[PDB]
Image (cartoon, rainbow, N blue to C red):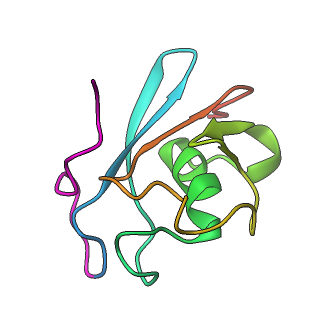
């Protein structure tokens, strides 16, 4: 029905070219899944990272909810960390700029 069978949008040395959708309200930034895991399964960092890096905003300022995962430095299992091109990650709070 939507993003799943991709794994080839935003490339990087360990990423399998994975690009995540980072939104806040609607405010969307293309973010890339965090390399040096197994490319397919992003690190615990990634879920927070994507929502964080999209605007450059610190972890406390964004409440990232996506992939049944919530933003933290080491939150939920890496296999579940968005194994698709980047998956989705949306933070509701503030993409502070």
| Residue 53 horizontal side relative to residue 18, left or right | right
Query: Does 9 lie within the magenta span?
Result: yes
Q: What segment carries the magenta color?
A: 1-13
Above or below, 17 against 25 in this view is below
Residue 9, position as x, y percentages in the image? 19, 51
Residue 71, position as x, y percentages in the image? 71, 50
Farthest residue to the front: give it: 1
Asked whether 14 or 78 is in front, the reply is: 78
Q: Residue at x 52, y 67 (%)?
A: 79
Above or below, 23 against 76 in this view is above
Above or below, 17 against 92 in this view is below
| Residue 31 horizontal side relative to residue 75, left or right | left
Farthest residue to the top: give it: 25
Farthest residue to the right: give it: 60
Q: Residue at x 44, y 69 (%)?
A: 41
Where the N terminus falls, by quadrant? top left
Where the C terminus falls, by quadrant? top right
Above or below, 65 against 14 in this view is above
Residue 72, position as x, y percentages in the image? 76, 58
Is the magenta region chiefly helix, strand or loop? Answer: loop
| Residue 86 horizontal side relative to residue 79, left or right | left
Asked whether 70 or 32 is in front, the reply is: 70
Residue 63, position as x, y percentages in the image? 75, 37
Query: Does 68 lie within the magenta span?
Result: no
Q: Residue at x 74, y 66 (%)?
A: 73
Q: Residue at x 22, y 63 (%)?
A: 17
């Amino acid at each position: 029905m939507a993003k799943t069978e991709e794994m080839v949008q935003t490339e990087e040395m360990e990423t399998p070219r994975l690009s995540v959708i980072v939104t806040h309200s609607n405010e969307r930034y293309d973010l890339l899944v965090t390399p040096q895991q197994g490319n397919s399964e992003p690190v615990v960092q990634d879920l927070a990272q994507l929502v964080e890096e999209a605007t450059g905003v610190p972890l406390p300022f964004q409440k990232l909810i996506f992939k049944g995962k919530s933003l933290k430095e080491m939150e939920t299992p890496l296999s579940a960390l968005g194994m698709q091109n980047g998956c989705r990650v949306m933070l509701i709070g503030e993409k502070s700029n």
